[PDB]
Length: 393
Ligand code: HEM
Ligand SMILES: CCSc1ccc(C(=O)O)cc1
Ligand SMILES: [Cl-]
Ligand SMILES: [Mg+2]
Image 1 (tube, rainbow, N blue to C red):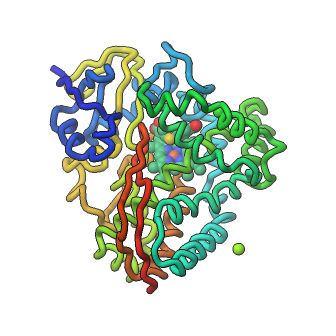
Image 2: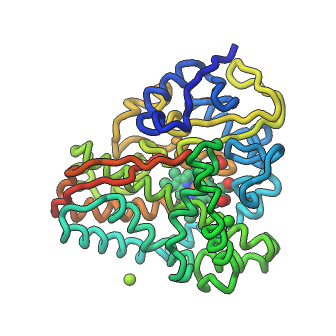
């Protein structure tokens, strides 16, 4: 009753161009079985949204990667928030929700916006740049570690650790195993910076520790929660900003609309998150035998969700493959949906918005002028290099 497919969603062939295969996964049925990895898969918007919003049936405490924590040991201690279900998930979630709250965004917006303006003016003096290394990567690295309260020493481990985290969600292919095997130096750096004395007072990490006073988390829980913000938020935001620049170069009419109304910057970034879906895939594990679509999934089975596919499903989106900066983007699952929906979404949107605002006000054209290279990762989509020429407005 359930179609079996041999598509490998963790192959380089898939990463290079997943969209034809995503249609095949969508059109094969509401639920598919991926024989290559012995997991179920859902690729349409309806089922992805349904799974995300049914946490008691499709749980996260057995891991949101391929590996099942009931069967295998986690490569690192499980995340206190991402790999927890209610009620264990709730109070750590509340802490990060307050640390990364709307109120918090007021304290960082001016600095984040000023840095984005300055970065774009710096790049305009160069003309031709790499929009990944010199922009999409450079800008978040220039604001987020400082906002986190990290010391200067050791920040060279941040990008390697982020890449490792998202590769480890995947199957035990080469990308995953090569990342985990010699990852101890990255883990030692991260674990050290999660300790209270190493975090600048007033930053995100120190604020997490400050919540131990309230009874929401214990002191021994706090380092693990800080770790979440050195795991998530970097590569996804980098990839999202890079995709936004790519779309503004490939859809030049949309850059001209953004220039004419820079207040579209926030939605222009949201549309890029839907278009790119920097977090392409992750898993749930069934706690019960379940009827999804017309399929009966057994208990203890891994269920792979295709967020990028859900955000390009023509059953839900008009012209899903077009980048449209005035599209009504509410309802996309690029940030997830339900109880786990990205707790850092306000930080990501802030970085994306102010960068696209700086582009909107300062740049007249963005032209690709060199070979474009893709960045390969088991669960992230994004570019490795994006040579562009920036024309000043
Ligand atoms: C464009 C940027 C981003 C994208 C596409 C993204 C994507 C996601 C997604 C899809 C989830 C849901 C995971 C699940 O349901 O299992 C999630 C959760 C999460 N995100 Fe993000 N994220 C982004 C930025 C950030 C930032 C900037 C931070 C931190 C500053 C962050 C921290 C987290 C954390 C801690 C969770 C776990 C939340 C929970 O389980 O309750 N993310 N993110
Ligand atoms: C799968 C969504 S991206 C993400 C990665 C790691 C964490 C964490 O370490 O808590 C949270 C979210
Ligand atoms: Cl670690
Ligand atoms: Mg300033």
